[PDB]
Image: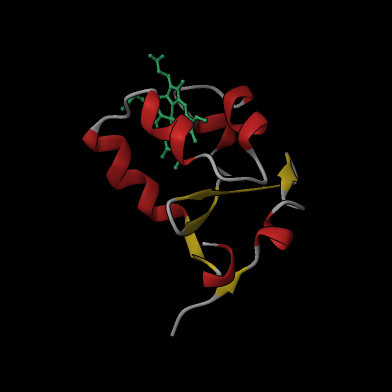
Length: 82
Ligand code: HEM
């Protein structure tokens, strides 16, 4: 099975209490990763609640960073918003 979230719902998780964001078609919960992010939490807060795919790709994340991102996946973006 798979759980789908709508863009509408994701936009409400944009704070230190709950930080979600979209990368491609997956939804990530980075709440417990904020203060652990080598890139700092400020950059993440700004992208919270939306599609950060471009920003994520542009900054040049390492292969190590990519594999680690997977541990934060909680579902997928509903096809209606893809
Ligand atoms: C899925 C969650 C993410 C993980 C697991 C993650 C992980 C990391 C790691 C391990 C680094 C260290 C350098 C490297 O290995 O590439 C890093 C650097 C960085 N990340 Fe992320 N990152 C995530 C999301 C993001 C997002 C969405 C943004 C941008 C909106 C971002 C912006 C940055 C920046 C600017 C740096 C610093 C690069 C530098 O100082 O040269 N990261 N990230």
